[PDB]
View 1 (cartoon, helix red, strand yellow):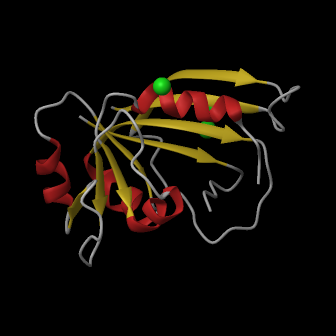
View 2 (cartoon, rainbow, N blue to C red):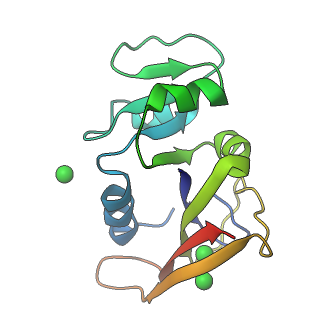
View 3 (cartoon, rainbow, N blue to C red):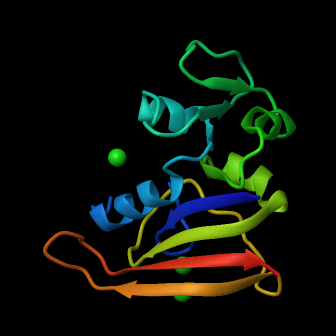
Length: 154
Ligand SMILES: [Cl-]
Ligand SMILES: [Cl-]
Ligand SMILES: [Cl-]
């Protein structure tokens, strides 16, 4: 099953905030699963995320034997093997091209106004069912209130 995970400020902007809570949610959901990423998230991460196979969806070749470089969506998939779930962690372009094959979304809705270049693709309500939502306040550690939600494609 293909699943997307993303943190969204208002307007579903993905790109400011300091959310340790969002990061332990991200970790708990991708640990021990393949994670499909875009070349820029790669360069911004800079090294393999531990505990996951890293597969990079890029047009030019890789320069890193530590991960899997894939030229397309179907090769992404194929590179993953026989696992119950594949996590799409981002790009905007990546999320856009995987949406149509996704069955689950894991979103962090951060109450925060921002001016960014990228958006999460628009998913359609009559298409997903919200099976989970959990609301949190800003705190000693997390600068903004946030909510965790999971949607399954109905
Ligand atoms: Cl760990
Ligand atoms: Cl949300
Ligand atoms: Cl919500």
